[PDB]
Image (cartoon, grey):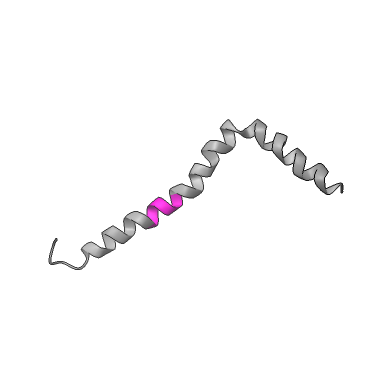
Amino acid sequence: MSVSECHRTALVSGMCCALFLLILLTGVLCHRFHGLWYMKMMWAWLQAKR
């Protein structure tokens, strides 16, 4: 809306930051599913039969 072009940097900056949050969010669930994590992983581990 603003004749200024710099404004573009903002719109792009917003997404650039949101992307970082995606990496942190993964941790939020990691905690809630801290136990289930191993429960499921166990299936993948034994499946290999190392």
User: Foreground: 14 or 37?
Assistant: 37
On the image, the x and y values in percent for residue 36 come to 66, 33
Is 18 contained in the magenta span? yes
Residue at the image point whose x is 76% and y is 38% from the top: 42
Relative to 36, 47 lies left or right: right
On the image, the x and y values in percent for residue 4 come to 15, 66
User: Foreground: 40 or 24?
Assistant: 40
Is 40 contained in the magenta span? no
Part of the protein shown in magenta = 16-20
Q: Main secondary structure of the magenta part?
A: helix
Residue at the image point whose x is 79% and y is 44% from the top: 45
Relative to 49, 31 lies left or right: left
Q: Quadrant of the N terminus?
A: bottom left
Q: Reply above or below: 47 against 32.
A: below
Relative to 45, 11 lies left or right: left
Q: Reply above or below: 28 against 16.
A: above
Residue at the image point whose x is 49% and y is 42% from the top: 25
Residue at the image point whose x is 58% and y is 38% from the top: 30
User: Foreground: 24 or 50?
Assistant: 50
Give the tally of numbered discs.
0
Q: Reply above or below: 29 against 50.
A: above
Q: Reply above or below: 32 against 14.
A: above
